[PDB]
Amino acid sequence: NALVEDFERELGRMLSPFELEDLQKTVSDDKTDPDLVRSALREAVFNGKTNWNYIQAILRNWRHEGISTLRQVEE
Ligand SMILES: [Zn+2]
Ligand SMILES: [Zn+2]
Ligand SMILES: [Zn+2]
Ligand SMILES: [Zn+2]
Image: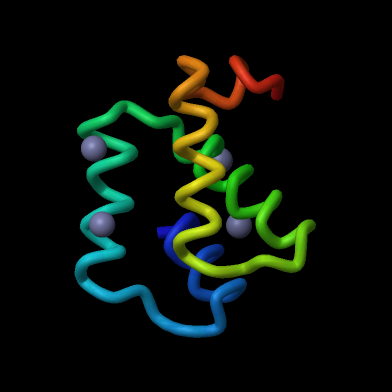
């Protein structure tokens, strides 16, 4: 999974089952574009804050504003 692979490379560690499951959920259940997830990861990297919770806070701030696809944030 390229996305998981992005996460593990930046995090420098494997995702836990819970994180793997959280990612599945956000993408399928919550219908979040994987490229939107990846751009939250990008933004955490660009901030020098590559940690799970920080990436999720970026995604939550975007979800609050009704943003679930990368086009909505701008491709
Ligand atoms: Zn990648
Ligand atoms: Zn969780
Ligand atoms: Zn959910
Ligand atoms: Zn993609």
